[PDB]
Image 1 (tube, rainbow, N blue to C red):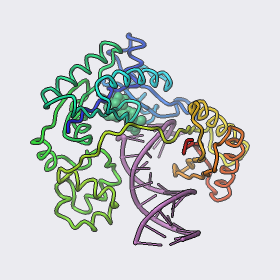
Image 2: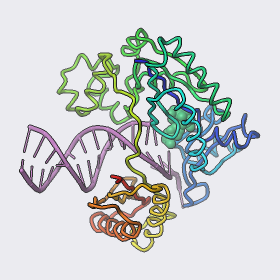
Image 3: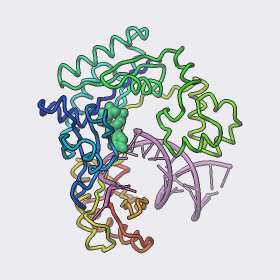
Image 4: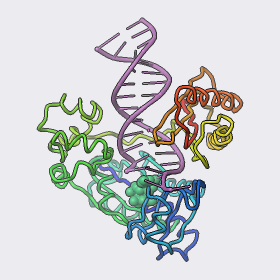
Length: 341
DNA sequence: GGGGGAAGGACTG
DNA sequence: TCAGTAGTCCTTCCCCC
Ligand SMILES: Nc1ccn([C@H]2CC[C@@H](COP(=O)(O)OP(=O)(O)OP(=O)(O)O)O2)c(=O)n1
Ligand SMILES: [Ca+2]
């Protein structure tokens, strides 16, 4: 099994670079401005010129501005990046019938039936980087290995504008050396739960009784790491089917006044319905992020498709429910729709 | 025991 | 006033068989 993983480099910012060439070379910081105060908000993606100085996704806009005060700060333009992404994904479709779009900038290709070895597999990923570059002027990084996970890990090592193959040999090496925290799907939370169990490398999962692990991080993540450690991971490339579509927003100020929150909720509904396009959801979920950044939610599943009007009146009921059951003020409010007809 | 949902959680990053 | 968005998978808890 030969998996070829494609990951677009600092995508949001790179697109801005393509639509405005005079930006390349200089630090570009694509941000999400909340409007709670000057430059309130967060960095969503920065290019390499910026990242080399510590300005990257997640940090506060105001912090970025302290480090790189003369960088070009741009507001997020999601729809624009989504259309560019659609065209590039279509380019990838032309190299394999088995494709798995994982996000707006990541796709796995099962080229097991397209190449004989990693040499051909390397040349194909070479052809792809040149195809995308030719038509969209977007650089991407290619990862190649025996399974999706290691294909991705490869791409993370080669970034940016890179390409790398991790053969059966290197896989065994990584299983022993690789900091398990660098394994896709393992965040800070799960990593710490591991150090405390004396597991810092994929291999270390083979030296501890299953239940001890399956009891610390859960059965799924257990069977996941173990399978990777034993070099038995082989999840197939599955054609992605969007299962949910939503929208969440930050309010100018925290609140718990149903009438002050409503405008933000309805806006989220309108945007969600525009993005549902033809898809009829049967389940709605209202999601609130409280003042202390905790996450709270209430949803409902109807035995029929949810019209916009039902969305409006039902979301209000779900928001009221949250307010009654939780006394904290809300900071972000949004809605997610799922279970499509 | 485990299905099915809801809600929470984690990671996507 | 440092803390954005989007989507998936998983777990927990409960109902229920
Ligand atoms: N706190 C974070 C961390 C990451 N991301 C998103 C946007 C950038 C991306 C980084 O993940 P990679 O797959 O490594 O991509 P990249 O080439 O490093 O960056 P980009 O996604 O911008 O191309 O994920 C985010 O929104 N918020
Ligand atoms: Ca990327």
